[PDB]
Image (cartoon, coloured by chain):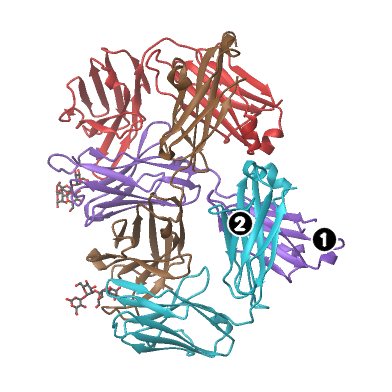
Chain colours: A red, B cyan, C brown, D purple
Amino acid sequence: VVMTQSPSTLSASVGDTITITCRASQSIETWLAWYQQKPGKAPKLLIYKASTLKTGVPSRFSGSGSGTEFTLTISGLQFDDFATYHCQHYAGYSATFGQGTRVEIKRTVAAPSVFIFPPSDEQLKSGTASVVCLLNNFYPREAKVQWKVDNALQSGNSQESVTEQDSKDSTYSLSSTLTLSKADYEKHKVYACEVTHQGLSSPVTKSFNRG
Amino acid sequence: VVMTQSPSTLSASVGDTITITCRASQSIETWLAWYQQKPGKAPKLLIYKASTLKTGVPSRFSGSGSGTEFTLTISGLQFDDFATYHCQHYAGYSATFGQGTRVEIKRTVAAPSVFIFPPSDEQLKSGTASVVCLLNNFYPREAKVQWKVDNALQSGNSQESVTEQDSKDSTYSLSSTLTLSKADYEKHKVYACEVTHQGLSSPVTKSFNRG
Amino acid sequence: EVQLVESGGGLVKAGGSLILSCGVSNFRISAHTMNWVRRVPGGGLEWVASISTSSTYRDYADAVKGRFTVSRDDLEDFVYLQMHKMRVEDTAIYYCARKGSDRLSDNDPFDAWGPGTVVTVSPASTKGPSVFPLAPSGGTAALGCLVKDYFPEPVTVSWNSGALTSGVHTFPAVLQSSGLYSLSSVVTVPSSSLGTQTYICNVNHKPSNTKVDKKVEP
Amino acid sequence: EVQLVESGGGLVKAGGSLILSCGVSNFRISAHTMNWVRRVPGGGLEWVASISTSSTYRDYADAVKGRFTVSRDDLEDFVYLQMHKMRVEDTAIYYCARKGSDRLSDNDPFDAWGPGTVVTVSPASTKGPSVFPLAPSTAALGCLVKDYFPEPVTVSWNSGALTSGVHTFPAVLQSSGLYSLSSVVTVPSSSLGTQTYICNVNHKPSNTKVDKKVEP
Ligand SMILES: OC[C@H]1O[C@H](O[C@@H]2[C@@H](O[C@@H]3[C@@H](O[C@@H]4[C@H](O)[C@H](O)O[C@H](CO)[C@H]4O)O[C@H](CO)[C@@H](O)[C@@H]3O)O[C@H](CO)[C@@H](O)[C@@H]2O)[C@@H](O)[C@@H](O)[C@@H]1O
Ligand SMILES: OC[C@H]1O[C@H](O[C@@H]2[C@@H](O[C@@H]3[C@@H](O[C@@H]4[C@H](O)[C@H](O)O[C@H](CO)[C@H]4O)O[C@H](CO)[C@@H](O)[C@@H]3O)O[C@H](CO)[C@@H](O)[C@@H]2O)[C@@H](O)[C@@H](O)[C@@H]1O
């Protein structure tokens, strides 16, 4: 049994009415639950048996469907409702989830401002080089960051984190850190960060030469 | 119930006959077991019910005693018998052990040869300084190593390990590593290892100046 | 031959938690009282915990009472040791031992031991961060602070003691392979102010009460 | 009201093991089927494991069957998850959750969850040592074999030619989680200008061989 949510990201505004669809690869009758999850918190049960609202859950949430097609509807989206929603087929001794639908605040596409920072000499003295790439205030959330060291595409030596949707302008920001030993860092010259995003006509590359 | 073994270390020669005593703080009848343990290995049950040899144990091991006083005897100490021995009071749902007796090969007191090694430049490029102190071929096993950096006694930044008793000369050796950042290492000049040991009339200091 | 195998040892920071497990080979635990014993760096053995058949009785050494829990799984032959609020003196090799003999009686010795697993508890429950400058387009320049190698979360970052808040992004921390957290905090400013305006990031790590002010110049 | 709390998360290297535990407050687990679920970095939830009342049935996701084991302790209200031979894609937040309802039925949803515990799996299952010389000022010289994982490391001197006077010390585990040892040898000082000294370090877990000559 495979559960598929639609869409993967749902953009909307406060006061809207929105619908998330969950499709089961085969009939699951009404053995379906909807959960809400806020970042860093535990999931909360919203709806079970396809349409039974859990006690305490506001009446703007509504579940419907049966068989292979199910819908969660929020009528009068409030700010507290922006979060990820999960559908779940649950059986006696197993369960399967959808991939989750993130409900975010709608706005217009915005390309990021990209900046690159070489490692500080203070940190280089310590034997570690952290190269940082900043993608500032972009929308939507999907972005691709590639590290190239002397044009060699890098993998496995970088980590990134993304901010929550900004309260003022509804954009996201991303930080990517490439970490190398001082030796490895000084074995190369050109350090570059290549950013792909919907709001850009072509990928943007920011680079620097060690020196 | 508190169990006390005596002695803590027993020095002997191959072919000797030795006795280790175990005292109980109160009468435990014959509810006592003796275990053998080699370094890095699991304890092995030798004797239980104070005097019953476990199947597979050589007949040179023998247990005796009852109440509060117990003895383990090895008649014809062989090389494989040099190890730690643990007594244990065992009850239905609890147990308590003595502190252990290390049976080692006896020899004459020998002071250590002391050597100090500054960090290699190759490691210094990595941002880490390891200063190493070696105490070579001493007896008995107990030794004290203190690090002094510009006469400031160090604590918490060193680790040491001790070799097993040497097969040829029955001495021990000890290695102590002081680890510092490159920054902290280059902020001081005099590095000193101070060794206290029975075979020395006074503590010995070996030093070097960064340079 | 009867075998036992521990699993789950490693490096823990003081105050943390770790759970050990023990599997067996060539016997069932159901008829055996199972035990946890530890060898301390001093070389002696300490009885840690005992769990009787059917989990009827669970006994603990005084040094670990209230912090450790022993559990058993007879259907799959597993023993568990939960260790919470760990102290430096919990550093030891941990063995699971079977109470048994050729014929089972009401009080048998520990006749089978696992090889042991090393558990080391470091005294440093917290570690303070290093702060490096992310030093400085058209009118907009970006600068920031890399707050690296701290533990645990969280760290707070402000710019100019709170004066500069617009355009500030403090990113979710990231957990490195060293077991230490790292994050960055950035701000975008008019580039024409890089030679007249001072920029200082104020990093506060309350778990270690560490405050660091770092000036970020080009 | 009803509470669950996980314990035991942390940083593990690929191929290693970690055991999680779950305690509860204000209910007993005996009547509840208990479950482990994980949230992956991508953001979705994955069912991991399920253990029925009396441990009659134990069910696992295909991705973890054969590597994970779930256990329960009804008398003290604990659930356990053993994770062995861990892979990078096991990185996730792990929650324990009970199946339950106002009236217990044969198929209830997950009505109570713990807050989750973070489990991170590093890609590097082994790491090879760095070898530095302990250069002489009877003289002593040696090799510092630092920052490898896991045990063991083997050291010989001159491929076995030099065995007398050699002390290879038990490794030490550093606060970084990586092992370090030293190997030393004492030689006549009058031989420092004619005899070559090379330590041969062999780390079989990473198939690493390193020869380092130690000059004054
Ligand atoms: O840790 C002790 C023992 O445990 C394992 O062996 C088990 C052990 O069970 C005990 C047994 O006690 C009996 C009851 O009191 C009964 O009323 O009377 C008889 C006769 O005196 C007692 O033997 O059973 C109870 C549960 O009823 C249990 O709590 C006890 O621990 O002993 C029996 C054999 O005596 C054995 O079959 C069990 O498996 C095992 O680790 C052993 O080596 C330990 O010594
Ligand atoms: O995971 C499902 C459920 O588990 C918890 O509740 C338990 C559950 O037990 C079920 C029950 O099955 C019945 C018996 O086999 C009986 O003989 O026949 C009827 C025929 O319909 C079965 O329903 O008992 C067995 C054990 O023998 C067990 O395997 C089943 O899962 O359900 C009962 C109530 O139905 C409950 O009392 C049990 O505690 C709990 O987490 C619940 O929320 C879950 O949905």
- Indicate the amino acid at tag 1: Thr
Mark 1 sits near ligand 1, with its Cβ under 8 Å away: no
Which-is-in-front pick, marks 1 and 2? Answer: 2
Label 1 sits on residue:
D196
Mark 1, Cα crowd under 10 Å, few <14 / some 14-19 / many 20+, is few
Q: Is residue C68 above or below residue B27?
A: above
B146 vs D49, nearest the viewer? B146
| Residue depicted at x 50% and y 24% | C201
Q: Is residue D202 above or below residue B86?
A: above
Image coordinates of residue C140 in percent, x first then y, are: 55, 11
Q: Which mark is residue B147?
A: 2
**Disc 1 to disc 2, how far (Cα)?**
31 Å
| Residue depicted at x 59% and y 75% | B140
Q: Is residue D207 among what the camera can see?
A: no
Query: Residue under mark 2: which chain is it in?
Result: B
Residue extending farthest right: D194
Image coordinates of residue C101 in percent, x first then y, are: 34, 79
Q: Is residue A14 above or below residue D113?
A: above
A136 vs C84, nearest the viewer? C84
> Quick one: quadrant of the N terminus of chain C?
bottom left
Query: Residue under mark 1: which chain is it in?
Result: D
Image coordinates of residue A140 in percent, x first then y, are: 44, 17
Give SS at disc 1: loop
- Indicate the amino acid at tag 2: Trp
